[PDB]
Image (tube, rainbow, N blue to C red):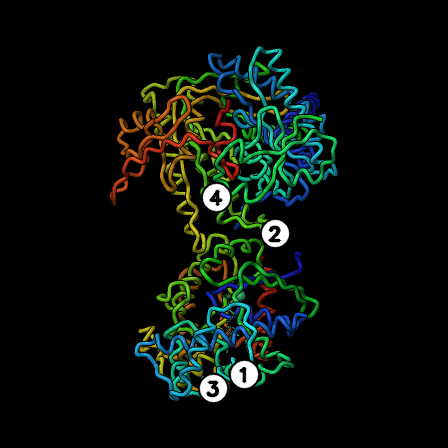
């Protein structure tokens, strides 16, 4: 117990904590039918959310092909039906809708509603998933989204060093449970969906997701029982941040006006071939939490920012390798 | 040389004193073990039978009796109960007002813990009959037993005592509340470890008590009723440390003036013509408490931080005249005016009430500060305030215990339970004394208080926004508490 490192994963909803747990299980560590079931549930949720939001957007998005209009209604018909059997008709209709240009245009405006992160990945894999002999790959398992309620513990070992990952729920109603893991915690890994700067949280549909994460990190950093606990900042969803930055449809400054005057720090270490815009956006997001950490960093604890992509196994492996020495150093400091 | 021998003898005496003081607040096992987050003593123990018992008819028995007589009768009854606990292999937790509760299988596991609890309850009924015979009283026992998992340990820093917290403890308290005087009210769980050795009948909770505000017929939970079957300096330093430990552990049980009065007599009893009582319950702790992770132990650690914060209020010089009596689950019990043995010059006769009211306000502030450190969850504190004559007494000879009794404590608990969250509900007379001292109150309405009918209650924080219209709460139906709170032993029965 004294030789094991207790790493508590914190952060707002859909930040990527469960995907970090999955990456730890992949690296250092009947059920397959359940995993396929949640994968298909994610597929159905994505398609129904997009179809419903087509008429709910301002302005509403019309279907590119009118002949697919009935295909929408079926998706609307079985939206609230639980324990769906997923017939081949549903798969065909979902594929036809996803190939429609109007549905894609509605998907490009997914920041105007609440859509899961694994939408495109599974809507482009419908054909493979729809098979009765569908075997979910490691990336398919990583992309699967399941809301986490409660405290989950995963014990793994790296280089004969024991780690105990405490995964919690990121929604507000779950945050009251977080204090149950604040005792004897070696490290806090705060996962942030860095690409969610243009999205609002599900709890109230008004608070910005990145602003919600910033407020949550301010609460965690200035917590009474976490005054001497260093927080390893996981700036997650870097790939989606890069796509959103290169797309240019949702500018960072349109939601965080201080980004316009921001300039890339000289200590930046971008990956080779990285676009300067992505580097600037990601380092602005990093400095947003660095400001909070330094506002009360009296030397009792420190913030370690890492640009992570949870669905990327190699990137998470490198990040955890870079974090292992930090974690053991803070355990010594404890 | 002779100083060393005297130091050794007095060190043996003080070691015995410290051992006795520890034994009064902890089980013998934990007492022997003794010899960011604050230190937290709690363990999850399964298969524990929790028993609660209420003295039915306590209000009439204690009527028209001096403090000495009432404390003597209570000491006799609780001594019989303690002998019974020793005989039945049960572990007494504490006594509150007219209530006595114990656990079997905690902290040492017992295969027949349910049998131990049932036997102890039946013996308690028998001993209460004997007490009525010898003391010419008319009182009974209402006993309730439930078997389940408990979280046993210590909460807070001041006046801490070994206790049990869980949903099963609350269910056992519910069993006691819904029971019948002279019978043991066992839960459905307890009957699973019991054979046909007892005369058992249906609990008939829905028939007897009528309405069930807890749930629809206890949420489909059955129940049963059982009616029966260099050297000098080193020695000086060591003895000084031992004496400091012994007196600090004695302060953990009884107030300082009680300690003075107990140096002459083996028993203590005082009748305070004017004393104030506050019960401050954390209403939504059940919302926070969840048994999914580590049986909720960590949750109670958070509670251990809140109660300890209240325990830091007593260390302030302003609240030196305030004595914490006990903590009951998520309820904090405090009193004032007991220490006022001498009328100090220049002090208001009711200054202790002002100090206790300020203590309740500071508890509200402490709760706000604690919520500032919680993540999207706010603990709500509900305080009940009353003042009047009461009887303070020490219960027990070997294992000491300080307690208070009277209609004042009952009315204070009533204002705690009938009050509103984040506000202090004070009694009518308490309003008459506080408002004369520059305090502003909102007339909440009338509350059904036993012995006074509809009595006016006043909520302290006068809400400038909106108005508190007279609620006029006339609910005289049995207030069934689904959790352990300050009403334990402060609600007299038939
Ligand atoms: N492209 C990409 N997707 C990611 C990344 N990290 C997480 N996701 C996806 O985002 C979704 C939400 O992540 P998730 O693991 O559920 O966050 P969470 O904090 O655990 O969610 P919650 O239960 O507390 S509300 C998942 O479907 C996951 O596949 C990432 O780095 N890149
Ligand atoms: Mg999660």
**Do tags 2 and 4 sit on the same chain?**
yes
Is disc 2's CB within 8 Å of ligand 2?
no
| Discs 3, 1: same chain | yes
Q: Closer to the observer: label 3 or label 1?
A: 3
Q: Residues within 10 Å of mark 2 (few under 14, many from 20)?
A: few
Mark 3: few/some/many CA within 10 Å (<14, 14-19, 20+): some
Chain bearing tag 2 is: B
- The circle on residue B16 is none
How much space separates mark 2 and mark 4, taking CA atoms? Answer: 20 Å
The mark closer to the camera, 3 or 4, is: 3
Q: Is residue A104 left or right of residue B433?
A: right
User: Which of the two labelled residues, at mark 2 and mark 4, occupies the earlier sequence position?
Assistant: 2
The residue sitting at 34% across, 18% down in the picture is B345
Q: Do tags 1 and 4 sit on the same chain?
A: no
- x, y (%) of residue B53? 59, 28
x and y percentages locating residue B432 in the rendered image:
29, 25
Element type where label 3 sits in the image? helix
* Label drawn at residue B294: 2
The disc placed on residue B306 is: 4
Q: Nearer the viewer, mark 1 or mark 4?
A: 1
The chain under label 4 reads B
At mark 2, the secondary structure is: helix
Callout 3 touching callout 4 (CB < 8 Å): no
Give the quarter of the image for residue B104.
top right
Q: Which residue is mark 3?
A: A96
Beta carbon at label 1 within 8 Å of ligand 1: no
Circle 1 residue: A126
Is B42 rendered above or below residue A216?
A: above
Q: Are marks 3 and 2 on the same chain?
A: no
Contact check, label 3 and label 1, Cβ < 8 Å: no
């Amino acid at each position: 117990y004294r030789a094991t490192h207790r790493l508590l994963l914190l952060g707002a909803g859909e930040s990527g904590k469960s995907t970090i747990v999955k990456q730890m299980r992949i690296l250092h560590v009947g059920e397959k039918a359940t995993k396929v079931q949640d994968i298909k549930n994610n597929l159905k949720e994505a398609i129904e959310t997009i179809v419903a939001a087509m008429s709910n957007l301002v302005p509403p998005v019309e279907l590119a092909n009118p002949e697919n209009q009935f295909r929408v209604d079926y998706i609307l018909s079985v939206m609230n039906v639980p324990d769906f059997d997923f017939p081949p008709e549903f798969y065909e209709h979902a594929k036809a809708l996803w190939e429609d240009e109007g549905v894609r245009a509605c998907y490009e405006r997914s920041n105007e509603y609440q859509l899961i992160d694994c939408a495109q990945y599974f809507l482009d894999k419908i054909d493979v998933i729809k098979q009765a002999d569908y075997v979910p790959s490691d990336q398919d398992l990583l992309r699967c989204r399941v809301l986490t309620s409660g405290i989950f513990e995963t014990k793994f070992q790296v280089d004969k060093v024991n780690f105990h990952m405490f995964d919690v729920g990121g929604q507000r109603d779950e945050r009251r449970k977080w204090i149950q893991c604040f005792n004897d915690v070696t490290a806090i890994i705060f996962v942030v969906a860095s690409s969610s700067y243009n999205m609002v949280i599900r709890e109230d549909n008004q608070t910005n997701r990145l602003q919600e994460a910033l407020n949550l990190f301010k609460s965690i950093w200035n917590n009474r029982w976490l005054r001497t606990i260093s927080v390893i900042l996981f700036l997650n969803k870097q790939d989606l941040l890069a796509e959103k930055v290169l797309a240019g449809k949702s500018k960072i400054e349109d939601y965080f006006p201080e980004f316009a005057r921001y300039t890339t720090p000289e200590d930046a270490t971008p990956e080779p071939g990285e676009d300067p815009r992505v580097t600037r956006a990601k380092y602005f997001i990093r400095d947003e939490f660095l400001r909070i950490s330094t506002a009360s960093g009296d030397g009792r604890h420190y913030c370690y920012p890492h640009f992570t992509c949870a669905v990327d196994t190699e990137n998470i492996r490198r990040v955890f390798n870079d974090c292992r020495d930090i974690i053991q150093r803070m355990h010594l400091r404890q | 040389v002779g100083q060393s021998i005297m130091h050794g003898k007095d060190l043996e005496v003080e070691k015995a004193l410290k051992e006795r003081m520890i034994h009064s607040v902890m089980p013998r096992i934990i007492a022997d073990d003794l010899m960011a987050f604050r230190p937290f003593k709690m363990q999850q123990i399964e298969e524990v039978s929790i028993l609660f018992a209420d003295i039915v008819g306590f209000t009439k028995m204690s009527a028209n009796k001096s403090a000495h007589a009432l404390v003597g009768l209570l000491n006799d009854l609780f001594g019989r109960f303690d002998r019974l606990c020793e005989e039945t292999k049960c572990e007494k937790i504490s006594t509150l007002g007219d209530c006595y509760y114990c656990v079997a299988g905690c902290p040492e596991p017992r295969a027949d813990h349910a049998y131990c609890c049932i036997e102890m309850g039946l013996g308690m009924i028998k001993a209460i009959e004997q007490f009525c015979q010898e003391k010419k009283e008319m009182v009974n026992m209402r006993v309730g037993v439930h078997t389940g998992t408990v979280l046993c340990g210590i909460l807070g820093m001041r006046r801490f005592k070994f206790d049990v917290w869980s949903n099963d403890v609350n269910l056992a308290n519910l069993m006691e509340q819904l029971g019948v005087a002279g019978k043991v009210h066992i839960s459905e769980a307890t009957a699973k470890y019991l054979d046909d050795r007892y005369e058992m009948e249906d609990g008939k909770v829905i028939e007897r008590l009528g309405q069930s505000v807890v749930a629809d017929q206890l949420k489909g939970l059955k129940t049963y009723l059982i009616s029966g079957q260099v050297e000098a300096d080193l020695h000086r330093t060591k003895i000084q440390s031992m004496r400091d430990q012994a007196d600090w552990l004695l302060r953990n049980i009884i107030p300082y003036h009680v300690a003075e009065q107990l140096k002459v007599s083996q028993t203590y009893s005082k009748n305070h013509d004017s004393g104030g009582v506050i019960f401050a319950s954390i209403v939504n702790f059940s919302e926070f408490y969840e048994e999914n992770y580590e049986g909720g132990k960590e949750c109670y650690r958070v509670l251990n931080e809140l109660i300890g914060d209240f325990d830091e209020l007593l260390s302030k010089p302003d609240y030196s005249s305030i004595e914490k009596i006990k903590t009951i689950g998520a309820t904090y019990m405090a009193a004032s005016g007991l220490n006022t043995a001498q009328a100090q010059d220049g002090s208001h006769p009711q200054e202790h009430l002002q100090i206790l009211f300020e203590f309740a306000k500071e508890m509200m502030r402490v709760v706000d500060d604690f919520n500032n450190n919680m993540l999207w969850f706010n603990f709500k504190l509900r305080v009940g305030f009353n003042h009047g004559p009461l009887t303070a007494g020490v219960i027990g000879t070997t294992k000491l215990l300080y307690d208070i009794w009277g209609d004042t404590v009952n009315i204070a608990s009533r204002m705690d339970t009938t009050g509103v969250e984040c506000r202090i509900q004070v009694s009518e007379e308490s309003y008459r004394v506080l408002s004369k001292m520059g305090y502003d109150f909102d007339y909440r309405g009338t509350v059904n208080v036993k012995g006074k009918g509809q009595m006016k209650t006043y909520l302290y924080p006068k809400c400038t926004d909106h108005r508190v219209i007279p609620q006029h709460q006339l609910s005289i139906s049995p207030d069934i508490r689904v959790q352990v709170d300050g009403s334990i032993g402060r609600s007299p029965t038939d």
